[PDB]
Image (cartoon, rainbow, N blue to C red):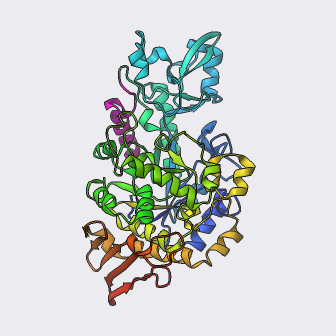
Amino acid sequence: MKNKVQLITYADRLGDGTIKSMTDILRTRFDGVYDGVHILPFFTPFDGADAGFDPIDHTKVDERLGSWDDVAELSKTHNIMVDAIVNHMSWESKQFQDVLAKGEESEYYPMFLTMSSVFPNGATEEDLAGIYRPRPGLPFTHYKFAGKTRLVWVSFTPQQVDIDTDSDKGWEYLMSIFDQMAASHVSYIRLDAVGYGAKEAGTSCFMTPKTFKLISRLREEGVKRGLEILIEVHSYYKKQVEIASKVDRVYDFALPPLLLHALSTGHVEPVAHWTDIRPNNAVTVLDTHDGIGVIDIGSDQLDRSLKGLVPDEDVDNLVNTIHANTHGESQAATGAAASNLDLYFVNSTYYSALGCNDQHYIAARAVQFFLPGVPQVYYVGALAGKNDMELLRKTNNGRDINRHYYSTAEIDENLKRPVVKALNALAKFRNELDAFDGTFSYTTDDDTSISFTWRGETSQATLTFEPKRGLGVDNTTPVAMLEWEDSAGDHRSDDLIANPPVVA
């Protein structure tokens, strides 16, 4: 994966509402800032229950957004990341509908998992009780094949039926997705829910040895077609290190809450600990299209005795600090859980979660960019966007607080803001200084300071991070200082908003 900053966006929420327009914005408003883009699911339909992640036909661009030719056009200037939903598909798909009608006589019967597919011999209570669940209850719902009631395996909703990724028909379907992505010159494939894609009786059915076999099989199919795969898994931070040592690339989901904690408390030991052990074959983010995940630095949720990167209490204080910093907005957007250790995510933009503090926000991005891994900026954060309470009240979907629709006019207005201009200059710096294509090191005081250093062929840069200096949502003291060396010698910026860095 290219070592340049990327944008994460919906095609329809950045510009006039189409892939073509989104491409226009990227090329004219963000030249040299974002060199690639993750286009969130744009298949048919894009505007369903789960905002693109529940398509009926994964292989067809929603014609309201554009066409595969539009993707191919974009590929001429940007590396493109797209989602491949490999674990399940719509119960309204023609394949599953054919099974409801014809049952075992269906061409696609072997394509879908039932309880019997995994447990042809029965299941004990321990067999079912042990399955790792992203949703309450057991992963089964009732469908009638012809007229016989079957328990279909459903990891998420009853409308999303799990495919047998070991079946010929299942693999044929997955490769039809890969083939279309290759034909339109996609570079990167985000494998959604791949951690659930392998079922094996007696195991948790989540990231088991069979799952890694499945991931390695997808990788090889991808390389044959010019595709690189990326896995998206939220798990206890020790699992994450284990997982990343077996796959090409993962997300760094610990960093977003680690930086909220650091900027709110002044403590840098957790960030230093994570820097020391974290997987470096990573994609770095602060915001995503989902909520801010706190699961990723807390205790293991199956065995709470495995403690996270900060004590349980600091996990709880991180949730409540977002609530305070947003003056209740994220409370309205986040469903309660009777305890914040039971939370998985907090619904809020990252800018709003920091209380809209520009110095803190740019510092957070700077740390992101200086840690090994490919950085991504979510489009709301690219525009330093505040919680969208109007859309939230209109849709009652909590995650829409962080999914504002940006018209081209709103984009240009926000490009006028010094915090946004600081972020664009910072990404340009991260793309243009060859120090980042070199070797990484870091030093630390104890709990006061941590310095990230990249030394390359013709350049060097060191980012010092001191949240202790500017505690408080209203503070204007910089907490990130920058020094670097380029063609024009030694340079320094003690304020990344007022004196954003530029490379010779």
Out of 306 and 63, give the one closest to the viewer.
306
138 relative to 436, above or below: above
Quarter of the figure that contains the C terminus:
bottom left
Whether residue 350 is visible to the viewer of this picture, yes or no, is yes
Q: Magenta segment: does it hold 205? A: yes
Out of 129 and 92, give the one closest to the viewer.
129
> Which residue is rendered at x = 48% and y = 66% of the image?
35
Q: Main secondary structure of the magenta part?
A: helix
Residue 208 placement (x, y as % from top left): 34, 31
Per the rendered image, the range of residues in magenta is 203-223
229 relative to 18, above or below: above
Residue 98 placement (x, y as % from top left): 63, 21
Q: Quadrant of residue 263?
A: bottom left
> Which residue is rendered at x = 64% and y = 57% of the image?
19
**Residue located farthest toward the right when viewing the structure as drawn:** 394
**Residue located farthest toward the bottom when viewing the structure as drawn:** 488
In the shown orientation, is residue 293 left or right of residue 276?
Answer: right
Out of 375 and 30, give the one closest to the viewer.
375
> Which residue is rendered at x = 60% and y = 64% of the image?
23
249 relative to 138, above or below: below
Q: Magenta segment: does it hold 52? A: no
Residue 77 placement (x, y as % from top left): 51, 66
Whether residue 228 is visible to the viewer of this picture, yes or no, is no
Quarter of the figure that contains the N terminus:
bottom left
